[PDB]
Image (spheres, coloured by chain):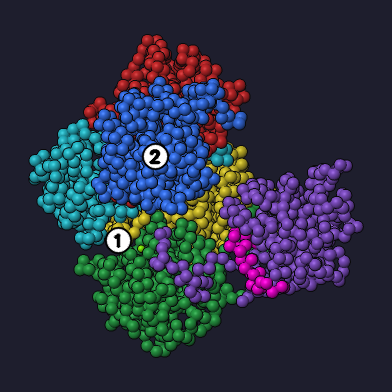
Chain colours: A yellow, B green, C purple, D cyan, E red, F blue
C-alpha cells in the first residue's frame, strides 16, 4: 500500500496493448453465454418482434436449423420460452405439463439432435393461464398454492421427462424450489439442475418480453440486502445455480451475491436491456462494441453465466 | 419459508415503504449542460433526444426552472468553436472562454446553485484527446497537468465552487489541489473522475460537445481504464483521495454499478456516478419507441443510490426532479 | 486513504448548502414513520396524559377522525395500544382475544375506512390481567406458559381475524414468536407479519407509557452482545421485522443489529424519550428542530422504521 | 445432499463450462528466453528438455512464431561469456551487452512485443551472487543497488518496456523507480520479484544461463526468502508497491501457490508468478517418460490463474499458446 | 504498519542463521507425515513400479518388515492401498468387504504388531470391480447407489472390524460419508475416524498410481470456491478430517480450506508429484533438498498432515 | 455429536500428533543471562531458584553447552557494580562496561550465537528508572533517548547482532534505527520491547540485576503500560514497526497471552514474548515443592507458540532445550 504518484503512475500498464493484456482482470468467453429463444407452435414459421429488433419467434424446425450454428459457435445452453397459443391457455394450466406442449416438444427435438447442448426450461404457470397469473385461482381470484405447486411439479417433471438438464423456476414465489427439488429427486431425476430466479425485481425492463411471448411478489428495486436473503433461501432449498434479474441495472447485486455466497451465479440481460442497446446501435448512436462492453461488465461484476439475447452476435465477435 | 416468507413484507404498499432500503431525492441530482457561444442559440442533438445545446442567455432562462425544482448543481460542458481548437489547448484557460463566461453569469444570477466546471483539454484540442500529444501521438501526462492546472485556476477565478478533472492523467488531482491551495482557493471542491473507463457509451456526448470529428476513430486506452478491471478502480480512487479530492466518481454508470458498490464500501467517502450520454440515449430511444415505460427513468436512478452513490450526474435530472416533486 | 490537511479540508463540502445536500448520507422521510396511539373504550371522548404532553387517549370515532389527517400526511402505519377498562381485566385474560375488545374493534374500523393504512397490534397479556403480569399465573403466582401461550395465540389470531396486517409480540419471552408464527400459518393467515420486540431493555424510559395505558425478562441496559443473540433467535423463529426498544438511548444497538443481520430493523422512540423532548421544547430549552434531529439519528444508525409519538409533527415538518 | 448434490453441475460439459471459475488465455503468458552472443548459435540444455539457448539472429526468427501465437511478452536472460564476468559486474550496464543488444533488435523488429529485461548481477559476477560482495563474502545491499540502477537505466535506454529486478536487495524497487523518473523514463514498468524464495527449484536455470559453475555450492539465504515464511511475503510485496512497482511477482510458482493467493487477496494489484526452471524440468521429464499426460501442462498453468495470478512466466509458453489456439 | 526502507530492511533477520531460526514461521516434523503403501496378495514378494521409481508393492510379510523402520522413525500412520488380483474383481464387489481381503488382512497384521501405528484404509469400490468403476452398475451400465452404498458400508465396517482407526472414503461422491458415519456409530465403532477426500480434482497427476494398483465426479481444476462447498458438506456429514488432492498443484486450496474451516486439514502429494520430483532428482536436475522444500510448502499452506510417498526419506532427513 | 465427536481425533497418540496445531522447537528459545564483573564468580539468586549470575569467564564455559543444545541466542543483562551507577547513566555506553565486554568475548568465541544486548538505563541509574530524571522526578523522554542511542551504538561497536530497547520511551526505536543506519550498522537488528506493562511480575529480575534497592518502592506507570489496556498495545506495536523494528515483543508473557495473539493477528510480523522472572520463579517454586510436575515447563512454553509468538525469552531455555532433544 502507500502507492503514490509519481512513484506509482497507473498509466504505465495502460501504455501498451501487451501490458494491458497481462494485467487484464476479466475476460468474456463463449462458455459464459446462454441464449434465450422464443418458440412458436407451428411448422416452417418465424415472426419478428417489434420491440426486440433482430430477435425472432421460431417454430421448432427453424429452431433446429438455427441451433446448428449456435452449437458450431460453442454456445453452451439455450433457455426456452414457448409462445402459447391462446386456445391452449386455461384455468387449470394443464398445458404446462402436456408432454406435447411446445416446451416439451422443443426440448425432445433439441436433446435428440444436439446431445451436448444444454436446455434450460421455464417452470411457471403464467404462460398457460387464461388470466396470465402465475398460479391457479380460487372462486374469488386468490391463489390456491398446492394446486398450483402440484401443476408446477407436474410441469418440472414433464420437462425432466423430455430430457431437460436444467429447470428454472422463473417465478418469484416461496415453496416451489423445494417442492420441485424434492419431486425431481423423488422421481429419479437426480441430475436435473435447478436454476433459481433468486433476486428478481419488479422492473420496467421486461416490457419487450411481454410482446415476445404474447402476454407483491417481485422485489422492490430500492432493496439490496433483501436480495441476499432471497439467494440464501434458494440455496437452502437446493438450487444448483442462482440468478439475478434484470441484469445491468442490478450489477451491484451480482457483485454482492457472488461475494456473499461464492456459488454459481447467473444474470439475465433482459429484453429491455437488449432493446435499448440494439435501438441505439441501429440509430448510429452507439458503436456495436457496446455489446461486448456490456457483457464483460457481467463477468467483472461476478457472474459465471449470462442469459443474453446478444449471445449469437457475441459468440461471433469472440474471435478478434 | 414457511416461517420466513419474504413475500409478507412485499404484500402491501405500507410495508414495502417501511422496509424500503434506499430512496432517490433531488439532493442527489447534478444536471450536465452543453453551452454554446453567441446569443439566443438553441440546438437539438439527434443522438441525445430531448437535450439541447444552449447559449448563455438561454442557459440562464432554463436555469430558473432547474433552481425552482431544487437541483443542487449543474456540470458545464462548453461547445468550443472549431477555430479555437489548437495543439496547445490554450482556450482551456482563456478567462473569456465559454466555460469561464458561463460560470461568472450563473454565479451572479443564482448564488446558491452549485457550478461544476470540467477540467480536461478534449473540447480544446484539434485531435480530441484529453491532454497534449507528443511527437509519437502519445498523450503526455505531466505536460498535460500543467495546462489542466491553469484551466482549474481560471475556473476558480471565475467563481466555480467545484472543478471536476475528467481527464484521467495520473497525479492531476494533487497538482490541482496544490495550485488551488497556493492561490488561496481554499474551499474550491475537486470532484475527481477517479475510475473513468475507456468506453463506447460516450458516443453521443462527443456529438453534443463537438469533439467527435476531431477524435475521429481515436481511442483513449493509454489513460482511461480497461472495462475488464475492477481491483484497479480501488487503486485509482485511493490515490485521488490521498491527493485531496473532496468527491470521487465512477464513470460510466449503469454498466459499472459493481464499481460504485466496491468504491463506497472500501473508502466510505462521497461517491458520485455519471449516467453518461449513451445511457441517456439508449433509454430515451426505447421510451420514445414505446418499448420501455417512462418509469424506467426513476428505476435507473434508484439503482445508483442502491449501489452506493451519493450523487448522480444525469441528463434526466430535470425530468427526474419534476417526477420526484409529487 | 492517507487523507491529510491541507490537501484534504473536510469543511469544503460543508461550505455551501448545495454540496452539503450532494454528500448528505441519510434522510428521514414519511415512509419511515409509525405512529403509536392510545385507544379508549367509549364514544366521543379524548383524555390528556399528564406525563406525555400533547398526546391524547382517543375513542375509536375520534381515532377515525385523526386518522384522516395521518393518512393525508402519508404515515404508513399505526401501532394500537388499547386502554383496558379495569372491569375487563381478569385472571384468564379472555379480553385479549375478545372479538369486541378495543384493539379488535379499532382494527376493524380502521381497516374498513382506510384500506391502505397499516395496523400493528400489540400481542401481550399484561393490559388484560388484573395483576398486570404478562401471563396467566398458577395458584402460587408462577407463570403457566402454555395456558398463556394459548391465550396469546388466540389473541394474535383475533387480531388477524379483525384485519391486522402486523402483530407485535411486545413481550420479552421465548416461545411466543414461533407459536404465533405457527398458529397464523396453520390458520391460513399466511401474510400477517410478525414485528418482534427483539432487543427490549429493562428501562426507566417507559415511565409515561404506564400512565397512558393505565398500568427477569427485560434486557440489562449494560449488555450489547446479548441483543444480537435476541435478534438472531427472533429471526430464526420467523419474525418478519425486528425492533430495538427503547430507542435513542440504544442507538449503538440499532447500528449493530442492522450491520449483523441486514434485516428489516425498527426502533421505538418510547414515551419517556418523547416526554423529555416535549417538556424541553415547551420550556423553551430546546428548539423544535430537535424532533427531526432525533429522528434522523435513527435513520443514520440503521433503522428502516421508527415508532414515534412525534410522527404527526414530523410528517408535517417533512416539507421544508 | 440430497437437495445439494455438487455432482449435478459436474454431470455435463455444458454445465461445467457455465460454472467454470477461471480460464487460462494467451494474455496470461510470458516466455523466458536464454540469449547467446554470436551468430547462428543454438544450444540444447540437458536439464531443460526442449529449451534452447539462442543467438540474437535465431531469437528474431523464433520470435516471429511467438508473436503469431499472440504471446504478449518475452523475459530475456543473457548467457554471459565467462570472460566478461567480474567482481564489479560492469557488463550488467554495458550498452553493448547481450541483453541490451537483444532488446534493441526485438524492439525494432516487433514493436508491439513486450520485452522484460532482467535486473540482477548474477549473470555478471564471478561468484554468481546477485549483488556485489564485501570482504566477508556478504552480498552488500546498497552498493549493489547502485549497479542495478545503472543496469536498469541501460535497459530503458535500449527500449525495454519493462525492467524486472530479480535480485532481492532491500529498497531496490524505489531506487530504480526514482532513477527512471529522474531520467524521464516515465512509462518504463518495473516488475518486481517481490516474494522470491531461496529455493532448490532453480537448478536448471543456473545451467541454462551459465552461472552454475560460478555459484558452485553457494547459497542466497541472506537475501532470498526462507521457504517456511508466508506472512513475511506480504511485507515484501507491500514495500515494493509503496516503492512504485507496477507489477509484483511470487517465485517459485507451484510450490508457493498459497503465497500467490494471499498476495492477490491482500493487495488486489497486478500479480505475477514464475513457473521456474525446476518446475518445467520435472514436468517435462515425467511427460517424456510417459508418466504424466501432456494435459498436465495446461493443468499446471490453470492452477496459477485459480490461485490469483494475472500473468505467468513459463518455459511452456509456446506449447501452451499452441494448445490454447483451438 | 508504514514499514519503509531503509528504516525497515527485511534482510536484517536473514543475515544470520540464528535470526532466521527465531523468525521462522513454520516447520515440518515427523508428526505431519502419512506414508501410502501398495500391498500385494502373496508371500515374500516385492515388485518395482516403473512410473514411481523407488516405490515398491509389498506382500504383507514384507510390509511388516518395512514398518519396523517406519515406526522407529516416528511416522504416525500408513494409508493402505491393496493391489487386487484380477480374479477377485467382480460385478458385486464382494471382495471390498471380505474379511480376508488384502486390506483387512494387512490391517489386522499391522494393528497386532504395532499397536500405536495408525492405519488409514481406502473405502472405495473401484479396486474391486471388473469394470473399474466406483460403484455397482445396473443392466445398462448406470450406478445403482444404495446397492453401492451398501457394499461401501460393509467395506467400512469390515475395515473397522479389522482394527482400522481411520477409514477414508476416497471416492468423490455424495451420501457415502454420512452413511459410513451413521453405520459406524450404529455398529458401535464410535471412535473410528473418517478422513474424507473432500476437494479431489480431475487431474493428470494420478497417472503413476494407476500403474501401482493395477487399474463427472472429480472436481474441475479451474474451481476454487467449489472446494469450500465440498469441504463444508463433508464436515456437516461428520468427517473428522478433510483432505485436498492432488497437493502441490492445489496449495491455494489448502490455504483457503484451513482459513475457512479451521478443521484438521490433510493433503495428498500424489503419485505424479512424487514421480516428477524423483525423476528430476535421479537425473541430477534437482538436488534432494527439494523433497523437504516441497513438504514444508504444505505446512506453510496450512496442512496438518501430508500423505506422501517421500515419508520415509523425509523422516530420515528430519535430523540435520 | 454423534456425527461429530471431537474425542475421535483425541483417542490415540498417532491422531493427536497428526492434528496437533503448534509445536515448540529449540529455534524458538532465547536465554537471558545475568553477567558479573570480575573473574571466576558464580552467584545464586534466591528469588530465581536454579539461575546464577556469572562472570564472563564462567559465561563462556556455560555457553559451550547452550551452543551444543542449539539455543539460537542469549539476552545479556549486566549486574552493574553499585559504584558505577549515576544520575547520567554514563556507564551504559562505556566501551569497557560489562555488557560491551561480554558481547566482544561471546562474538569471538561463538560466532554463530546470537547476542541480544539490553538498551535501557535501569542497571546504570542510582534511582533504578529506565531513563534520566528531571527535577520533578519524571523520567524524561527525549533526553533519555539520547543516552539510549549512545548505548545502542556502543553495543553495535562491540559486535552485537541485535540490540533490544526495553525502556518504553516513546520514539526510541526510530531514533536508534536512524543512528544505526547513519553509522553504517545496516544489519544490526532492533528487537523492540513494544507492549511492555507496568507489572508486579518483575520482582525477581530486580534482585538478579541489582536494581531492586535503587528502585525501592518506585513505579514506572508514566512509561510502562497499564495492565488493563489491550487496544493500546496495538498502537505501541504499530509505531515500533513504522520506526524500523525487526522484531516486536510483548512483556510479561503468560499474563498477557491475549496481547501476543492480537499482536500476531493484527501485524503478521516477527513477534516475541518474555516469560519474565516472576513467571519463572512461581513455576520453579511450585515444581520444587512438588505441587506441579516438571511437564509444566513445556506446557508453559507451548502456550506462547499457540498464542502466536515466534520466539520466547525464557530462563527455562536450557532445561527446555534438553527436554526437546528427545
Ligand atoms: Mg488516477
Ligand atoms: Mg524486498
Ligand atoms: Mg512505544
Q: Do the residues labelled 2 and 1 touch (CB within 8 Å)?
A: no
| Residue D68 visible, this orientation | no
Residue sitting at the far right: C87
Classify B232 as above or below F257: below
Q: Is the residue marked by circle 2 packed among few (<14), some (14-19), or many (20+) residues within 10 Å?
A: many
In the rendered structure, find residue F126 and report the number of the disc placed on it. none
E153 inside magenta stretch: no
Please tell me which residue is depicted at 86% across the width and 71% down the height of the picture. Answer: C44
For label 1, the residue is: A6
Q: Quadrant of the C terminus of chain C?
A: bottom right
Q: Which image quadrant for residue E23?
A: top left
Q: Which of F247 and E45 is in front in this view?
A: F247
> Which image quarter has ligand 1?
bottom left
C291 inside magenta stretch: yes
Task: Report the number of discs.
Answer: 2
Q: Is mark 1 on a helix, strand or loop?
A: loop
Q: Which of E81 and B188 is in front in this view?
A: B188
Where residue D299 appears, as percent x and y from the top left, is 35, 39
Residue sitting at the far top: E44
Please tell me which residue is depicted at 47% across the width and 63% down the height of the picture. Answer: B269
Q: Which of E260 and E72 is in front in this view?
A: E72
Q: Nearer the viewer, residue A162 or D106?
A: D106
Where residue E284 appears, as percent x and y from the top left, is 22, 28
Where residue C1 appears, as percent x and y from the top left, is 42, 59
Please tell me which residue is depicted at 81% across the width and 44% down the height of the picture. Answer: C143
Magenta region: C282-305
| Residue F283 visible, this orientation | yes
Q: Is the residue marked by circle 1 packed among few (<14), some (14-19), or many (20+) residues within 10 Å?
A: some
For label 2, the residue is: F123
Please tell me which residue is depicted at 30% across the width and 33% down the height of the picture. Answer: F102
Classify E242 as above or below F163: above
Amino acid at each position: 500500500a502507500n502507492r503514490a504518484y509519481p512513484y506509482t503512475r497507473l498509466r504505465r500498464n495502460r501504455r501498451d496493448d501487451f501490458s494491458r493484456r497481462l494485467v487484464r482482470e476479466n475476460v468474456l468467453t463463449v462458455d459464459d453465454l446462454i441464449l434465450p429463444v422464443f418458440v412458436l407452435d407451428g411448422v416452417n414459421q418465424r415472426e419478428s418482434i417489434p420491440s426486440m429488433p433482430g430477435v425472432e419467434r421460431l417454430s421448432i424446425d427453424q429452431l433446429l436449423i438455427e441451433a446448428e450454428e449456435w452449437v458450431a459457435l460453442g454456445i453452451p445452453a439455450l433457455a426456452l420460452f414457448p409462445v402459447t397459443p391462446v386456445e391452449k391457455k386455461s384455468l387449470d394450466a394443464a398445458e404446462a405439463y402436456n408432454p406435447e406442449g411446445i416446451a416439451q416438444r422443443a426440448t425432445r427435438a433439441l436433446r435428440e439432435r444436439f446431445p451436448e447442448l444444454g436446455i434450460i426450461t421455464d417452470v411457471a404457470l403464467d404462460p398457460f393461464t387464461t388470466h396470465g397469473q402465475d398460479g391457479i385461482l380460487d372462486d374469488d381470484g386468490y391463489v390456491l398454492n398446492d394446486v398450483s405447486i402440484d401443476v408446477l411439479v407436474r410441469q418440472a417433471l414433464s420437462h425432466a421427462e423430455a430430457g431437460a438438464q436444467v429447470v428454472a423456476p422463473s417465478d418469484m414465489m416461496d415453496g416451489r424450489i423445494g417442492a420441485i427439488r424434492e419431486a425431481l429427486e423423488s422421481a429419479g431425476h437426480t441430475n436435473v439442475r435447478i436454476m433459481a430466479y433468486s433476486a428478481k425485481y419488479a422492473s420496467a425492463y421486461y416490457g419487450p418480453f411481454r410482446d415476445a411471448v404474447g402476454s407483491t411478489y417481485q422485489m422492490d428495486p430500492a432493496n439490496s440486502d433483501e436480495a441476499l436473503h432471497e439467494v440464501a433461501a434458494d440455496l437452502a432449498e437446493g438450487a444448483d445455480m442462482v440468478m439475478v434479474k434484470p441484469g445491468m441495472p442490478y450489477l451491484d447485486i451480482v457483485r454482492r451475491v457472488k461475494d456473499e455466497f461464492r456459488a454459481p451465479t447467473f444474470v439475465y440481460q433482459v429484453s429491455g436491456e437488449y432493446a435499448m442497446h440494439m435501438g441505439a446501435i441501429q440509430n448510429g448512436w452507439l458503436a456495436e462494441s457496446v455489446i461486448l462492453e456490456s457483457l464483460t461488465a457481467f463477468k467483472r461484476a461476478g457472474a459465471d453465466g449470462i442469459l443474453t439475447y446478444f449471445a449469437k452476435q457475441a459468440a461471433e465477435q469472440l474471435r478478434r
